[PDB]
Amino acid sequence: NREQVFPTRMTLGLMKTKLKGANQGYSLLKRKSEALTKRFRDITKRIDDAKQKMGRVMQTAAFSLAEVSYATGENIGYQVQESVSTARFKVRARQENVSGVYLSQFESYIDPEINDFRLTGLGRGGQQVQRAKEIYSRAVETLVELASLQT
Amino acid sequence: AEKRTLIAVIADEDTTTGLLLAGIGQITPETQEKNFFVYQEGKTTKEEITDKFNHFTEERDDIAILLINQHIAENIRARVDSFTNAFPAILEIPSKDHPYDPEKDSVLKRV
Amino acid sequence: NGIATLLQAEKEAHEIVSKARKYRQDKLKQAKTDAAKEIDSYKIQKDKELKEF
Amino acid sequence: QVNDELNKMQAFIRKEAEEKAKEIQLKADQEYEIEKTNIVRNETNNID
Amino acid sequence: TLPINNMPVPEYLENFQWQTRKFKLDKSIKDLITLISNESSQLDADVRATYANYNSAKTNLAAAERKKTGDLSVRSLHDIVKPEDFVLNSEHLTTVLVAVPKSLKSDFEKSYETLSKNVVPASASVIAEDAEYVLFNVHLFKKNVQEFTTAAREKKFIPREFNYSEELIDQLKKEHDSAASLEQSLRVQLVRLAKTAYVDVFINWFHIKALRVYVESVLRYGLPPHFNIKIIAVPPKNLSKCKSELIDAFGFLGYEPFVMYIINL
């Protein structure tokens, strides 16, 4: 309940200054928690909105991919797996300073060395496969944004 | 980290194919493995899915965001809840005939 | 049915396996004690030399 | 017979655990030789 | 959500005053057309995705209802496989709990008692006996459980994760409740999206119709158009007569030479 500090006038002054510092730190950290919890509520609202957006985008992208597969006459899964030598979509971490914390937020990046697509050599539904690739690129961008939000 | 620039998907076959067409991951020349670890929910095994998820979320993996379909992540929900680390992030992508449910979101459950 | 007999034989043999490991582990503990007894003789011999000094 | 097949499975299950019983005893037997030098040598150093 | 009967779409048709949100006033005609088409197409795609998600949620709810209906092929695994017949508390033993119709269930039981290693056919016992719910329980080896399940699947039998005195029933009830809640939420989201879309897509469609009318007018009568763009709401019983009268009146401008459009919405 009490420290073992030897009672002296200097010790009393030091401990009174420590009490003042602790009270100031308590007020400061309470206000920081209030600001960060307001930001936390905002982030939760954006998480819910982005979850609804992801629910829509996955459905529409899957519909586009299914239409492309139907047009091509076969699933493009084998071609996509064969074309997995290099990565065309990458996420670069950015330590964006939000409030008083260095929260890490992802930023999507792309490279031209992996521009090959599964539509190469398919022989049918090239436009549909390209449209599905673009739709899933937009979907991956949305998921990178949501992943930054979630981190 | 700098090496974190990679996206991992453990979703169903259709979702894995779509994300591979998007170009999420690459096959490691040295490890002879790719981030597009396609695995059907009905095929393989729950233990295999858990092992793949552990490998992707640990062992100094380069994956920045782990993509797991809600259907497949439901079977490994214990491991998903255990993965309380800030990174890599995990998402519950909807699957065909398997829409994403807010109750099944492990990360959103922390609210 | 016959499933109980199949499980009982495995369970009975498993209990013997633990007993065999425990007995062997106990013998390992006894072996260390016996080895320390030989080392104690060297300490006893050293103590006699110290007494002689 | 069904009972005969179950009895045969009982012997195989018991035999499988019997093999582990020998392995457990053999592995601990090797540790006994290791323990004959480990700790005892340290005890002599403490005695020294 | 505002009811469809109270939707002001005809009231907007009575005015058709273009807004700034649907298209910028200073934007180019081609640019405005592109923007409006893109926005309306995105709205339509979102509505279609919401409808698909609602359909998937309804399918999941129907599957949960079928599982709760008591059909052993989808019912609780506790009653599907007898606890005594199913192998439990044994590290080297496991159960199959295959569910199949009478002939298929008999074939699966025979395969489990024959093909599976350490089958122990004396432990085989059927806990259900309906025509399509004649599921039986067996106690095979722990390592042979996968082989027995594969054989049952080849024998048109669906295994189940049977467990004696476990929380399987509570887990199934919780899963059904969660599926119902998710289906209700998805239905609410789809209803709200459709209610907003029936107005937004309609407004975008009317903007496209107005832009096309202006383009046709400037193409026909030259620049400036100076055309008396008017909207006529003929009664349903005299639509053909009104169209004939309009065609007759449009002959002075010499499809009819005058810009004419037919809308049934």
Image: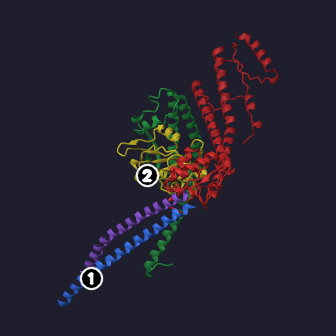
Chain colours: A green, B yellow, C blue, D purple, E red
Instruction: Please state the horizontal and vertical placement of residue E123, each as a whole percent of the image.
Output: 57, 58
In this view, C31 is above or below E217:
below
- Left or right: E219, with B2 as reference point: right
Which element is circle 1 on?
helix
Residue type beneath disc 2: His
* Most foreground residue, A121 or A33: A121
Q: Badge 2, how many Cα within 10 Å: few under 14, some, many 20+?
A: few
Which residue is located at x 58 percent, y 48 percent?
E108
> How many tags in the picture?
2
Residue at the bottom extreme of this rendering? C52
Mark 2 and mark 1: span between their CA atoms? 52 Å
Residue type beneath disc 1: Asp
* Most foreground residue, E149 or B53: E149
Which residue is located at x 26 percent, y 82 percent?
C40
In this view, A137 is above or below E124:
above
Q: Are marks 2 and 1 in contact (CB under 8 Å)?
A: no
To which chain does the residue with label 2 belong? B
Residue at the left extreme of this rendering? C53
Which residue is located at x 61 percent, y 32 percent?
E41
Instruction: Please state the horizontal and vertical placement of residue A41, each as a whole percent of the image.
Output: 58, 53
Instruction: Please state the horizontal and vertical placement of residue E132, each as a whole percent of the image.
Output: 66, 46
Which element is circle 2 on?
helix
To which chain does the residue with label 1 belong? C
Q: Which residue is mark 2?
A: B55
Residue at the right extreme of this rendering? E237
Q: Which residue is mark 1?
A: C40
* Most foreground residue, C42 or A148: C42
Image quadrant containing the C terminus of chain E: top right
Between disc 2 and disc 1, the foreground one is 1
Looking at the image, can residue E235 be seen? no
Instruction: Please state the horizontal and vertical placement of residue B27, each as a whole percent of the image.
Output: 40, 42
Image quadrant containing the N terminus of chain E: top right
